[PDB]
Image: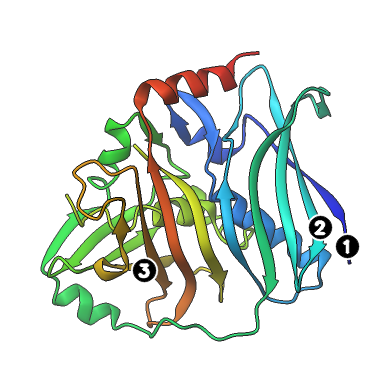
Amino acid sequence: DQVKTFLQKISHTNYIVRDHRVHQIRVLPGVTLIDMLYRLAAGYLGERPIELRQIIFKQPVVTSEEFDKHLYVTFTPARDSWKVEITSEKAKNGTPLGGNRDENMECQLYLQEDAPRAKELNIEAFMKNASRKWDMHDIYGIARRSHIEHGEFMKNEGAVYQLQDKEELMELTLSDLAEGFREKFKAHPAFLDASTLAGSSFALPYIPFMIDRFCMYQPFPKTIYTYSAKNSRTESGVSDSEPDVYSADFTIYDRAGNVLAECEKLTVKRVRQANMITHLEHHHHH
């Protein structure tokens, strides 16, 4: 235990980027990296359950016909924990190109030893005593009109329930294609991505940007239930019609009401279209 850099490959043909494009450019969801860390940890620590804290998402992983990407995950020993950083580089036909390295993400990895703090929930009762409901395609309408396009593998099926304007529950299921990989992941990126959409009904381009804590307690089943509460949401200046940042907590349930995952304070940042266009097109250019 100390320092250990691991190599991961994100190719242009990877189903994630294929089915996640922003302004017609293939990018890597920032939350996707949460799965990567969990897969790699299992190898570098032992399989010992672990969580993540102080996550920062920082340069999008973009692919092209012209280039794939190689990612470098580096575990560095630290204070009763490990620091983790992910960088990346252009590659082609299996070989990196030797250019500049982008920083993609950082966090602090701790050993998990504490039980979930989020009390179970009666899924059935929430749904039946649901107050408002939206299809699992109108919620995505927000991404679409912000020029984000989910394809087969990344687009979840289901519906969003709202209770008194105060709580939300997202019934999510993978596409059959996506479903075939659900056990190959530690946390399916499709599930993770869609879950960052928690709280969308409250208030019906905001990009993930920091996470105070994320923790997997159990592997995802075929359908999950992402719960989110209004009282856990805060935002810049309190009462902004167009906030700069806002942030919330979500909990992922199974169906029997067990805690599968916890996310504390997912902070997201709205982006100017024009800034994002410049940004992604710079990334796309070789």
Numbered disc 3: secondary structure: strand
Report the residue at 89% width, 67% height from top: 1
Per the model, the C-alpha gap separating discs 1 and 2 is 5 Å
Label 1 CA crowd tier, 10 Å (few <14, some 14–19, many 20+):
few
Q: Are dots 1 and 2 in contact, CB under 8 Å?
A: yes
Q: Amino acid at mark 2?
A: Thr
Q: Is residue 32 visible?
A: yes
Q: Are dots 2 and 3 in contact, CB under 8 Å?
A: no
Numbered disc 2: secondary structure: strand
Whichever of callouts 1 and 3 sits on the residue coming sooner in the sequence is 1
Q: Amino acid at mark 1?
A: Gln
Numbered disc 1: secondary structure: loop
Q: Which mark is residue 225?
A: 3
Q: Which mark is residue 90?
A: none
- Residue 28: x, y in percent? 56, 38
Q: On the rendered structure, is 207 left or right of 135?
A: right
Q: Nearer the viewer, residue 243 or 169?
A: 243
> Compared with residue 155, is residue 94 higher up or lower down, i.e. above or below?
above
Report the residue at 21% width, 64% height from top: 161
Residue to which mark 2 is pinned:
76
Whichever of callouts 2 and 3 sits on the residue coming sooner in the sequence is 2
Residue to which mark 1 is pinned:
2
